[PDB]
Length: 181
Ligand SMILES: [Mn+2]
Ligand SMILES: [Mn+2]
Image 1 (cartoon, rainbow, N blue to C red):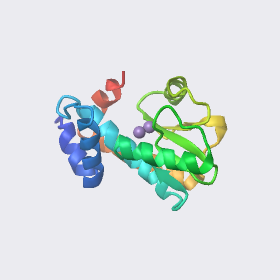
Image 2: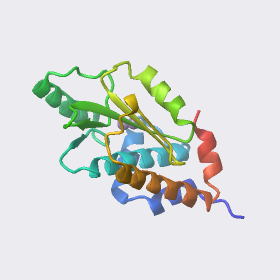
Image 3: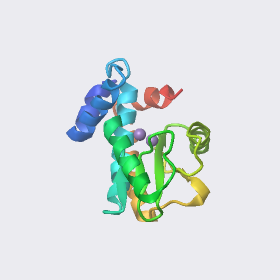
Image 4: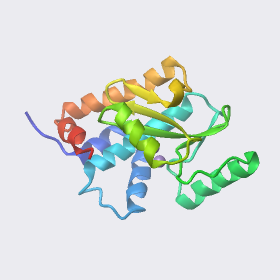
């Protein structure tokens, strides 16, 4: 019953652009992706989920995730200067053009209401919509408003499902699940 390397899995079941954005993301904090390999996969995963979330409806969302902080804040500032909206204190992951609000996407290996509540306490602003996903098909969103339809979110959760089980087949899942706090 062999145990695999998380880094290899990350470089084998994730798209090279995703991986590059993850590497850049960790580098911008100086973190080494060889000490924090579960964080590497968590970031690749979160990235992919945000991207799929935007892909579910083209021309509806603006992506903030994966950008430089300078540029991401530039986009946020532009949007808010266009709408007059409150500049959130923390960088959100998306902007919904249809409901005209910012979205924070969270992905958790733990219970979704816990992650949701921790996000809610952390981000201060009650104007930023929150959407949390798990690797087990569970999701938790603000005001029971899930933005996307069932098929799209099922697409996302199916991808997550795949990630989790492909992790499992390499023995990576237990440590990855345990690593969160
Ligand atoms: Mn983010
Ligand atoms: Mn997020």
